[PDB]
Length: 59
Length: 69
Image (cartoon, rainbow over all chains, first blue to last red; front, top):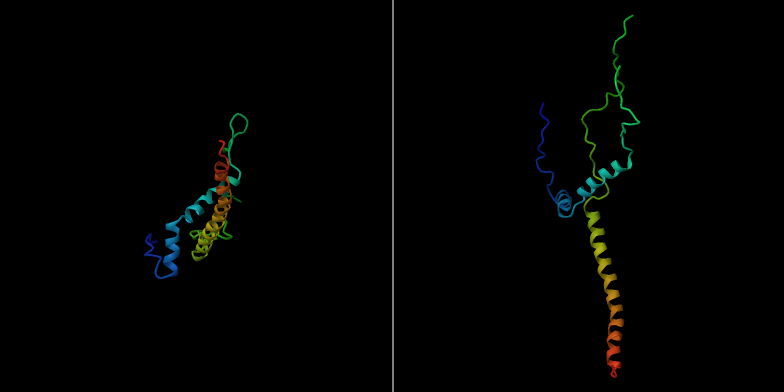
């Protein structure tokens, strides 16, 4: 079917080059990656402590 | 009647789609804030350094004024 992993260079001229250069000069996308686990901290953990709570099973 | 496992369609979950999208910063917009913070940064910092000069001369004046020391 072919999905293709290669993007064949997203940058071309002026507008497409400068924004791709801005993320490599400072960070931006790493701060975007930093914010990915920020929301993960905010949501409740799906944790079960054994001596009191028990896990799901089958008949 | 014999009952078995039933099928469900509705929306079919929607498989294979790019959820990643650019947010907040575009490119040209963040540089205006970046250099803008620098221009505000140096201007506000040097005003305190000029205010330090008012103290600097006056502090060293104490040694000149006091000769019985």
